[PDB]
Length: 193
Image 1 (tube, rainbow, N blue to C red):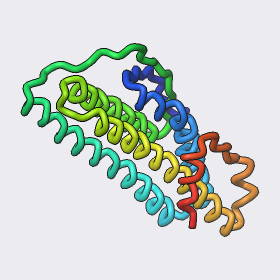
Image 2 (image 1 turned 180 degrees about the vertical axis):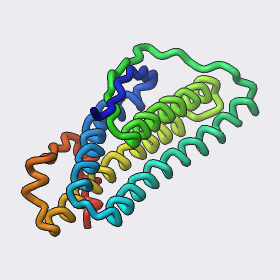
Image 3 (image 1 turned 90 degrees about the vertical axis):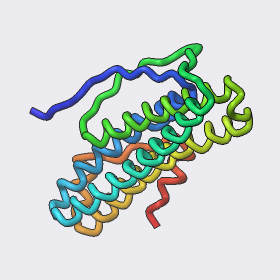
């Protein structure tokens, strides 16, 4: 009755498979709880407002990932590099896609994995310092982790919105909240204030 997309996703770089590991399950559970809590609140005004804010936070990170990919791909042709590296142990992850936004987050991880492959090419080809590879490794990792925490923060602020509409006990039954096992994500979840 409800459509669900099951897919296998290969991730090459360690930065993107670490981001995938400590966030994708919690994020796709958060996107699920949001779609359920919003259907309990009913008000199409709030539904479209929350659907929008989630869309634009995923859009901003996607827009920045493309800009960083476009700039760094220019540095490759500027420097005459047409190849990209193999990886010691890539991982395959079987994922379930219930929302199209869940697909968007998983697509963001692929763009991250792609951008890391470009960074690693420029670093192996002495175009990028060892220091500015780590600065890109940390910041883009932390960039997706900030999104994970913000999405969950939107979920948490939706639960208080549902509480303020008396629909609280309904939420506890329909979609209970999941523990956030990653501290970086859990701390960022306090975009509630």
